[PDB]
Image (tube, rainbow, N blue to C red):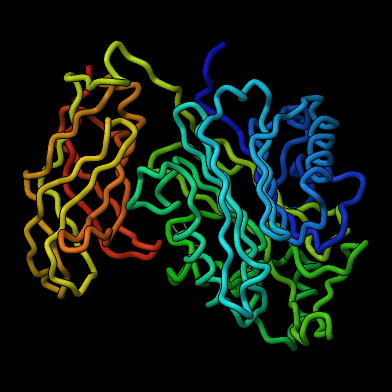
Length: 460
Ligand SMILES: C1CN(CC2CCOCC2)CCN1
């Protein structure tokens, strides 16, 4: 029975509007409706992993698990195993997997973050799940961010609080937040970003939707505009949107958008918006391909339509050699040449690096770099040829070239990370000096750059 080198992952996000679902929701799991939809010929082919995010979910965990499992069984005739379920208030995440994956899945983590203070603490936040699938780390975040057209800044703050404080993945990766802990990170939910056009344009917007002319609407979508100005979701991807806005519908039809201000909306307009989204971030040069991104047309119990996205994702096997794990392989080494960090910080402390990777027995601390002034004000931290030689646990190129090195630059004074990034070992050549580069972030905001050269020795 060979270990897979690809799996398919289903991501679902649905704000259920505090209403039970209808008796049939199979269209969701089948990626059928509007947008980038799945070929009919694939309908019986199960995804390897189904991750279901709900918001405003009125069901017990038991009630929803029964509906989900019975839905997948009707579609595929496969009885899926429950990997994890985690609920914060009415925000829920369910991970189901094919039974053949039960012994490939380990290190299952769940967490939640509550966003806001006092007034704004009580129903918004995120839940998440992580685990290993053989040699590949997977993370999944379902967030319900602050509502309202005039609160995009609050949403961006919610995002930063969730990525700082959601405790998923390998706790030994202490300088790194969830945006660096996983081979593949999927972040979805009712992100609540709106189409930011004048209220008076509501009927014009509806007209455009009926014509399936989304271009002039997406150019005003707050998530796309905020992403373009690097205010939120820096270094995350989203598939092109080719489905109608998923909010706000009259219930029991999809023929009408309910946008007008009502006591029930706190006298706020809800212009048709793409509230319900799926984004991802994968380590550099790892295969990840979106194969569907769309909304259902036939599930109408909520004022939101369900959104689906499916992905092909590269995975690696749990590698054993004669040597590692449990020793080094002297035939392998990672050298860094002519490296320097460029930092936006106005501080003057000394900095050192930490190298973290599951190809090392444990993380490696460098010597302090040498601080110089950049020609445009910047701090440049030079490491020269001083950086340690990294000693991987396995030298086999079929293992090593699939690995990644996480880099933190830390203050000698405080031991706090000023920047985090990631370098792929999927090089064009071994035993050859090649350029490397990573942006550096902290709390998911750009704080600098790391660049230099790498020289990788494998057993071949
Ligand atoms: C793909 C997407 N890119 C920028 C997007 C920002 C928001 O709107 C769409 C473009 C980041 C890197 N490459």
